[PDB]
Image (cartoon, rainbow, N blue to C red):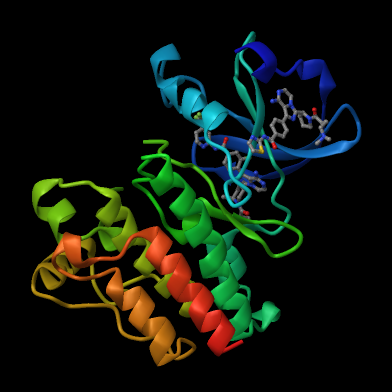
Length: 255
Ligand SMILES: C[C@H]1CC[C@@H](c2nc(-c3ccc(C(=O)Nc4cc(C(F)(F)F)ccn4)cc3F)c3c(N)nccn23)CN1C(=O)C1CC1
Ligand SMILES: CN(C)CCCC(=O)N1CCC[C@H]1c1nc(-c2ccc(C(=O)Nc3nccs3)cc2)c2c(N)nccn12
């Protein structure tokens, strides 16, 4: 992997952050100074060299609102993934911590951060396919970034549009739909979407035009933006560039 190969001698482990999806994650330092997150890949859990297409993705895709890969430790097992350290951890847990007493300006900033990452991915013709608050991380400054980008019952039924559930029709518009659901997760302070329903019931209600209600903290203008991601006809949903312009407009008007 050329310049992406990190010498494991340069890593120092400081704390186990937890068991994320895929393996153990630890907070550590690179060459004793730079903060990093170190993910140990679980043995055989995932798969082969051919799956290290995800590394080809992470080594080529880069944005300020995407969790940045710093390098990998592959000349040894278990494999280490070295990434940007996100001090506030998972966005979903961050939203659920009632001690933050979030203002709606902060919630809209979280949407904007994710929308920027997604506009970038849209521009690179990349499909996240599992966009949700559980796959977003928060740094020490409260900046949200998208992680696990195109990694890849457990299917994300509640973040999927009708055409994905009925026909497996994945497109940039199914990422748009998931983003509206992620804005709803943010404005509901991390509620499970369709929390009264099972996945099978959500899929039937979604096929029948049910839509997530406006969270109390979302204004009618913010709700219009998330609702525009859920047009039954995929071609009627906006692009991330349009969503970003809409969020910027609401921030200028409300903020
Ligand atoms: C979930 C729990 C426990 C774990 C916590 C956690 N995971 C990551 C983290 C997230 C993703 C990756 C990563 O390597 N991603 C990846 C890897 C590939 C692959 F290598 F396969 F190509 C492809 C795509 N994406 C590496 C990471 F260190 C990070 C991170 N960078 N910083 C801080 C915390 N982090 C989040 N949580 C919490 O904060 C909860 C609240 C306590
Ligand atoms: C000054 N300091 C941070 C560097 C000195 C600290 C340092 O070397 N560190 C700190 C953690 C492990 C190690 C490390 N970091 C990187 C890296 C790569 C890309 C970007 C980036 O921003 N890329 C972008 N691409 C497009 C837009 S932005 C930022 C960092 C890399 C790398 N590619 N191979 C090996 C080791 N690497």
